[PDB]
Image (cartoon, rainbow, N blue to C red):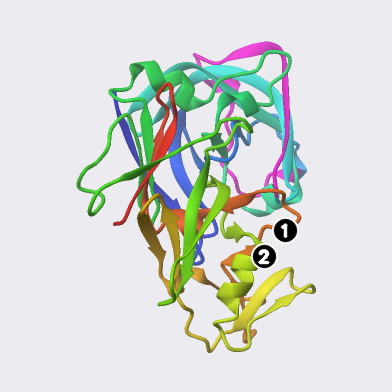
Amino acid sequence: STGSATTTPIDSLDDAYITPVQIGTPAQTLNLDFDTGSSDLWVFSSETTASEVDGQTIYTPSKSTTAKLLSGATWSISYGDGSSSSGDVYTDTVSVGGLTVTGQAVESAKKVSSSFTEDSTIDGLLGLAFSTLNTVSPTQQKTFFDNAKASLDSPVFTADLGYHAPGTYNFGFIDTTAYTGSITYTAVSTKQGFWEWTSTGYAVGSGTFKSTSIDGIADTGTTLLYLPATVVSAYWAQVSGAKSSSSVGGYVFPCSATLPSFTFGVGSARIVIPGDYIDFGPISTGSSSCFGGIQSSAGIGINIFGDVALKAAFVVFNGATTPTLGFASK
Ligand code: NA
C-alpha cells in the first residue's frame, strides 16, 4: 500500500503545515500537524475542556462506530516550545492520503496549553518520530508510520514541504518526479528517539564551505533552523544591522535587508536554503525589525533542522531495519 496527502502552510510565514487526516467511521477529517520530532497522534476532541477550544475541528469518538476506549491509558506531552497537552486514548481507524491503519491509538486531549487553543488551524499532531518517544502509559503505543510500515510497498515516508506553497507527504514510495539529481542518504541514530543525523558542514551565501560535523534532528514540527551559536553568528554577521535581541528572543535583522542563502552538507552533497526562506517578517505588526529563520540552539540541548531547512529539500525518512535519512534538491 501507499498514501499521498497534500500539506498546506497554516499562514503566510509557513509557521507550520497541516495535512488532512480521516479518523473514525464515518470519517471525521481533522487537519493535523505532522511532526517528525514527536511520536503521539493526539487530537482536539469532544473531551477537550471547552474553554481551551477556539475554532478547532474536534474528534468525537462517540460518533465513530470503530472507536474503542483504550481502557486505563493516559498520555501527557511537553514540546520544545513549552506547549503541552494531555488526555485519554481511543483506538480507531486512521487514514492519511488513502493509506489506512486500523487500531491506531488516537490520543484525545482533555487539556491543551494556550499556544494550541490560540492556533485555530491545527486540530492536533501526528507524530512521525520513533515509537520509543510515545507518551501513552501504561502501554506505550505505536506511531501511524510504525503501524502502517509492514503494509507499505517500501518502509519509508517522504516530506516535500513548500515555501509559501503546499507540499506533500508520501507513505510507502519515492516519487522520482518530485526532486532533481540524486538522493544522498545519511546515517540515523535512534538513541534519543529522533531522526538524528550529522550534517557535514555549512556555507553562508557564496562563501567557502566549512567542513564540520553538526549533529541534529530532522523535525517537521519545528518552524526554524536551530544550529550552534558559532554557525548562527557566522550567518548573521553577513547581514548589516543584524543582532541577537534578548528582548525579542533571537536574531533580528532590518526588514530592508536582502538575506544570504545558507548551505548545509549531507555527506558530499549540499542543500541550499535561499535567503528568502530565512525571512520570518516583522517581529510585531508594522515593525521594521524582522525575525530570523536561523537561530541558536544553545540552551535547547540539540540542533534542529526544522521546516526552514527541510522545505529546501525532498526528504526521505527511511524506516527500514537500519533507518537512514535521504536528502535531494528540488
Ligand atoms: Na515567533
**Residue type marked 2:** Ala
Residue 91 position by quadrant: top right
Residue range corresponding to the magenta coloring: 52-80
Name the residue at 36% across, 51% down.
Answer: 167
Q: Are marks 2 and 1 in contact (CB under 8 Å)?
A: yes
Quick check: 320 left or right of 223? Answer: left
In the image, what residue type sits under mark 1? Ala
Answer whether residue 156 is magenta in the image: no
Mark 2–mark 1 distance (CA, rounded to whole Å): 6 Å
Q: Which residue is mark 2?
A: 229
Across and down, in percent, residue 233 comes to 63, 73
The spot of residue 152 in percent (x, y) is: 33, 22
Instruction: Give the image location of residue 173, x and y in percent.
Output: 28, 32
The secondary element bearing badge 2 is classed as helix
Give neighbour class at mark 1: few <14, some 14-19, many 20+ (Cα, 10 Å).
few
Q: Is residue 321 visible?
A: yes
In the depicted view, which residue is nearer to us: 255 or 8? 255
Q: Which mark is residue 298?
A: 1
Q: Of the numbered discs in the image, which one, if any, rests on residue 250?
A: none
Q: Residue furthest left?
A: 177
In this view, 3 is above or below 253? above
**Residue nearer the viewer, 261 or 105:** 261
Residue 178 as seen in the image, left or right of residue 35: left
Kindly identify the residue that appears in the image at 35 percent across and 26 percent down: 99
Image coords of residue 284 (percent x, y): 67, 77
